Image (cartoon, coloured by chain):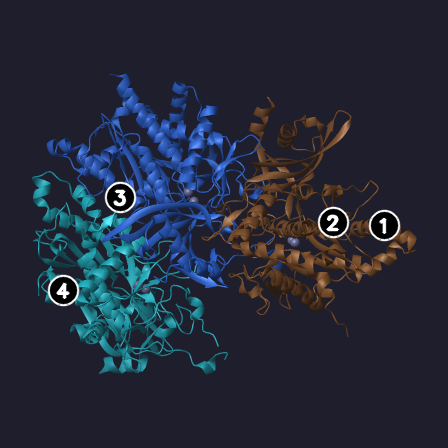
Chain colours: A brown, B blue, C cyan
């Protein structure tokens, strides 16, 4: 129990270090699924899907979808079980025209992606992570890169020169080199020359060959364990790469439980794990939670899996989908606010979250969180079922912000509206959310992984124990 | 020069990494001097000094002073050449009563030492550095420790639980987290003024029981090691550059001069032998220098007085001269070269620079001028040091680049020890440094070439000052 | 009985405070207390031919007190200079040189606000006088220290009725102007030279000095509350009075010092090896910048002059230098700065640092500050805490202590500790006792704390050198 907790956190830290951007999160989660026997399914190909098989798809190399069609997945008693995460995080991203030269220093123009605590980005060893596009002969090559060396620095202004409000335009401009070193190394103009020198060396191409790029600035300080008892994990992108890790680990674990049982109710469901892009910016895109992509994927799965059923029983995709929705559920997973010891005015006295105290069941009146009491009562029952078999408890705690105070929104409600499925919003407690370096607790990583697993395994079973009004 | 500058920068980084606090910078500087054949000297022994000998002293293990008495140091033509730096930086230090328990989290009570940019300390992998006192039998053991693992964290409040503009309460919000009550209990199943998770960490590091730790002076320290940055590896980034980068340069400049004297003696088996060379690293600069180990202390004057008393014991008693008469004579040819970091021209804040006195990376030694004497620099004295750089160039064929600095007239700036030491010692002097950005932050940035220029400038000062003085024509 | 002794120290402290209504009278009373314990009065203007195993007392300008005892075996090799400090000035309303004010048929006195006092507390109090008077007697310029314990002056508040009724903003120049008489009574009395002085004031001063009004040349007089300090509380556990800051601390420095001297003069140890110093500086309340303040060269000169006398043979026969002997002794020397501390105020909890709260009867406040407003460093406080432990081992009486610090956001007052540490190149700590209402005409402290402080001073003097020999360096 304690051995497996640290193991998950160690694996979680390795995954976060390798996934410095949304693009690298897709690649890493895709490779993780490929290694568990998942088939690389594309959008621009005919879907000829088989039952008792897993499939993997990265839409635009920035949206991760993993799904497993159950051995005996049926229209009448089956469920579409979706657990969601988001593979994007707040970042400083390089602007299209980034060449800035002020006070003899070469700088990079950067965009402010998401509502980040930008002051934390100041005075940090910065690397790069993203997608680049370069000409190679007659082709347009897309390559995913990550520079783990410190090449950029966003310097603070000395206290001595002041009598703090950051201007996001003028003050957030990181330095890359000096005009002197740029001149010594020398001996389209919209791109910074020291940046193109770095990118050319990385891609093994000419500076001239670099066309366009989508790159995040990334702290080179690897995530690690903190505290005298090494009970804490600290690092960038915990929101929501720590959450997405737990979604995919719990999903992989269920797929392996099905594979393991093959080597009984667990065979009649469609199991989906999805890591969206564009969450930090409001989800409105083809790869974000508001996209038709998810609904289309489900329709395409239904069409392939029930090809004979729709033609023989005269059913439509819409008819099948409506039936499945009655037994379907969405478990949205995103980071939660741990009760801050230095800011007690921010916590609602009765809905306080503590480190190692388990999964945060997130409630919001204005439905910023999809959670409803009945749906949460069902998920708590799957954890009770997990406890009866595994003799291991899944810890939980209810969250809510103060009535007079506003809070952030999750994809839960967007996806629930789009798919017309019930759902709840969960996650694990963390501090400093939207900082370049956040902090979470080791046992909560364990609780979330087993929490997502217990949901996939027991939702359909709990559903049969229900008596309506 | 280009390869040498990178070698200097590498050594500077290693010294800054090994020195997470004033205590450790002073120990590392002492060891460096001993390794160069410097004799250990205690304040509590009779000083029976010799010419052509180097000595090292550590007042209270937080003040560092190195001195070399020239083979021909004399009352009539000699000079006292002093180069200063400071070994303290802005830091979050552990409070006497540090035990804090709020929202099921064990916290440590901390103090804000100096005028640091405290927001930069939030969300960092923090360790410890400094002095610890514990009982081992019937003895009070003083041990200097440095824990380079992440043990402490100052968490920011999330943006979601906030109504851009950053406003920190230094008492309430600067309280790092050490553990949960759960794990503290678990480890307890596997005086009260001190945090138990903290005593556990210290006792393990010292190899004593928890009840043994009496008192400690511990600096929280960024565990992220200083490194090189920029596409061309032309910048250095790390904590304590102010003033462990300047202090490193003072000591390397002083060691280089001593080695040149030792090599000159080995070669000639000339004017370099007639002076007393001193290099001092004070503590408490960040807090106004008022202490027994700070620039306002009587210690410096007392050390000079003791060297004079010893070295000129024959002349005092035979020629019937006093320490004061000898001191007064020497001071006429003496000089203080104060070294502290300067402000590079910030590319994102053009409103902060005085248009004609702008500093740039790799553009040399910053000659710091202030009208209110926040910097001791005077035109004549700057002129003299600028001539030592010319004499260096003539001989070693390497230019020591310089650049004049000043803040805008309507704007205030921080002071240096320069003027304090000049008043105390009755000596002339200047304020020099190297340009850096993000001063008083937990991670500052500087340039590689400047490190090279500073070391070469300190060596040039020590070598040519007395020579330069002999070419002066009075009014 | 420790409790009986605590009450006795407290009773003695109050009598001393009552008689010391100014820096001048604190100095005379502390000097007289030292002379009664067999200390030799020393003048700065005479050749110091000191003897070892003797106590000396000097009063620079009759406003700075210094007591010192030279140990029989005070030596260069193993000797320590142990200094305990207090300050003998307090916040006060002091008579201005041109004090003659006449408004609304009332004779008033022009006063200076000395130190950062809680001036509203000075209103509606029975005021007397304490200080120095200069007068001509034939061919002589006579200095005379006086104290008038009768209520002669009054600083009246303005009636609440004549105001908007509630907050109070005092104009230090306009509203701080005490009344001495009416023009009617001044006219009747003279009917029964220099116009810069209030005539009713010259009349008061001349009756006291037994001279003529025209003979009064100059004076440096503090206005002083005539209400004597006393015990308070249902159980008489508190002491209340003026000038606790820092005549209470200064009393405890000198009593600790007298107890040490008496322990040597018997009226492991290694007690005869040291030079023991007790000093009461003037001017702490205004920054300490004077020849009689803690920024003065006098302390360094006093030590140098002691070194010159006690080590005359080592200097003139063995060819040692004052500076060499000084440098050597500094390594084993220490400063115990004593000044009042802030007790946790029960009505203003927002002013306390939660983990560093001071409480009445709970011991000696060991005061910490990062900006070095207090000279205290964690290693040096540890050495002092150990002297208290050794005291307990011998006398089986505990010296309670409690750590103090202000909130990180909030600023605090400075002490003479860091000034003397830089001046003398010596280590040291800042201690004191908890009180409430610092800078008020009437402050309050606790009886048990008076006991602990006196013992803490004694224990430092007695055990520092012993504690120092038990130290293992890095
Ligand atoms: Zn999120
Ligand atoms: Zn977010
Ligand atoms: Zn500084
Ligand atoms: Zn500095
Ligand atoms: Zn005071
Ligand atoms: Zn005081």
Q: Is mark 2 within 8 Å of ligand 1?
A: no
Q: Is residue B78 above or below residue A359?
A: above
Whether labels 1 and 4 share one chain: no
Q: Is residue C142 above or below residue B339?
A: below
Q: Chain of mark 1?
A: A
Calculate the distance from the C-alpha at mark 2 to the C-alpha at mark 1.
Answer: 15 Å
Residue A417 visible here: yes
| Cβ atoms under marks 3 and 2 closer than 8 Å | no
The residue closer to the viewer here, A233 or C160, is: A233
- Position of the N terminus of chain A, as image quadrant, is bottom right
- Write down the residue under mark 1: A303
Question: In this rendering, which labeled residue sits more in front, label 4 or label 2?
Answer: 2
Question: In this rendering, which labeled residue sits more in front, label 1 or label 4?
Answer: 1
Whether labels 3 and 1 share one chain: no
- Write down the residue under mark 2: A67
Q: Chain of mark 3?
A: B
Residue C246 x/y as whole percent: 27, 66
Whether labels 4 and 2 share one chain: no
Q: Chain of mark 2?
A: A
- Write down the residue under mark 4: C34
């Amino acid at each position: 129990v304690d051995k497996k907790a640290r193991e998950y956190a160690q694996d979680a830290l390795k995954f976060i270090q390798r996934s410095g951007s949304n693009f690298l999160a897709c690649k890493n989660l895709k490779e993780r699924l490929e290694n568990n026997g998942f088939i690389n399914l594309s959008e621009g190909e005919t879907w000829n899907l088989n039952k008792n098989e897993g499939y993997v798809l990265c839409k635009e190399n920035r949206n991760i979808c993993g799904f497993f069609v159950g051995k005996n997945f049926n229209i009448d008693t089956g469920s579409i079980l979706i657990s969601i995460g988001h593979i994007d995080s707040c970042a400083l991203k390089i602007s299209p025209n980034n060449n800035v030269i002020k006070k003899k220093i070469h700088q990079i123009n950067v965009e402010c992606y998401g509502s980040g605590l930008w002051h934390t980005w100041f005075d940090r060893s910065l690397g790069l992570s993203g997608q680049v596009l370069y000409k190679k002969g007659n082709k347009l090559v897309e390559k995913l890169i990550q520079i783990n060396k410190s090449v950029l620095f966003l310097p603070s202004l000395a206290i001595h020169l002041q009598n703090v409000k950051i201007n996001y335009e003028n003050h957030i401009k990181p330095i890359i080199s000096t005009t002197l070193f740029n001149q010594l190394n020398k001996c389209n103009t919209d791109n910074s020359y020291p940046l193109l020198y770095l990118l050319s060396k990385e891609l093994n191409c000419k500076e001239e060959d670099i066309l366009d790029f989508e790159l995040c600035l990334m702290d080179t300080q690897e995530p690690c364990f903190t505290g005298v008892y090494e009970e804490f994990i600290e690092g960038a992108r915990f929101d929501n790469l720590l959450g997405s890790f737990c979604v995919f680990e719990g999903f992989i674990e269920l797929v392996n439980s099905i594979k393991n049982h093959t080597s009984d109710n667990i065979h009649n469901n469609l199991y989906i794990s999805i890591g969206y892009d564009h969450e930090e910016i409001g989800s409105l895109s083809e790869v974000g939670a508001r996209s038709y992509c998810t609904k289309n994927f489900i329709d395409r799965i239904i069409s392939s899996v029930f090809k004979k059923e729709i033609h023989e029983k005269n059913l439509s995709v819409q008819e099948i989908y409506g039936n499945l929705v009655n037994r379907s559920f969405i478990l949205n997973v995103d980071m939660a606010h741990c009760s801050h010891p230095n800011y007690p005015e921010t916590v609602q006295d009765n809905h306080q979250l503590f480190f190692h105290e388990g999964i945060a069941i997130k409630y919001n009146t204005n439905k910023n969180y999809v959670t409803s009491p009945l749906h949460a009562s069902l998920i708590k029952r799957t954890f009770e079922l997990y406890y009866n078999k595994y003799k291991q408890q899944i810890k939980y705690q209810n969250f809510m912000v103060k009535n007079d105070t506003p809070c952030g929104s999750t994809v839960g409600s967007m996806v629930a509206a789009n798919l017309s499925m019930p759902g709840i919003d969960i996650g694990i407690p963390q501090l400093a959310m939207h900082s370049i370096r956040e902090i979470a607790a080791v046992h909560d990583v364990f609780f979330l992984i087993k929490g997502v697993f217990a949901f996939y395994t027991y939702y359909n079973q709990v559903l049969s124990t229900c008596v309506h009004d």
